[PDB]
Image 1 (cartoon, rainbow, N blue to C red):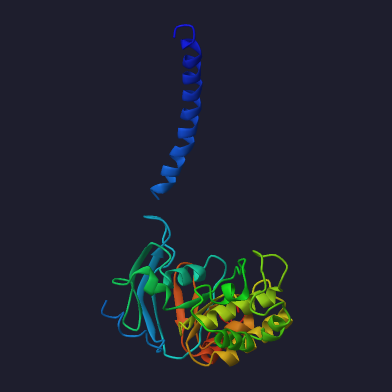
Image 2 (image 1 turned 180 degrees about the vertical axis):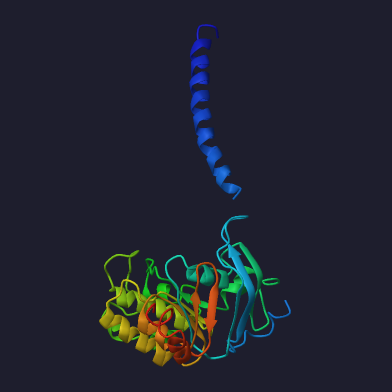
Length: 283
């Protein structure tokens, strides 16, 4: 045993060094590891909402993003929101989906707020189309309805309404084209059409349109907005963009000031009351 103890010793020490470096690699995994009364009543189609004295902050105890935000929205009425970059419109959308964890005030939808509802119900109640679209890999059924609850005629109707049925029928199999993450399988307008098909199948009855205009040709964006208007006669939509005509077509609009907002109900009244200084030439 003494003629050979040395080799066992060396195995021991070298394997110990290796095990230590591998355990140090493992430790970062644990470092990452430590990071119903209104439910039974179906969510109402009445999109009347009211956010009374709202504020929002990004990080705990930092500079506030909003300041004394008070607004109300009537049922079945299209709402627009304006403001420059960093004015707080993306923050307002994220707070409407309570994505910011340092908001103050009470925010409501039909007398209902985020005090007693889990996230799952909070995401089966509103729809949203982001400025950054993506088409994750899979088939068309996996992009339209990843949950897959919706039936085939439903997806076909959502594609026909979204002006996408013809190009879908021109693919192998139909509703089963193997898509790749991003890629070059569809056009930007067709990606936005897929986003609008997601919005169609969501059936939230409340829509949020977070810059469905950026990085889209005007000749296609205008007909896109025309289709989204002719299709959305109900199910109140709140939009945000930097286009003139998009803000012009909305009824209730609130100009985002430096830290606060100033709301206006009638669109044709506020675009000439300021004498075209802060709401018309800015739009």
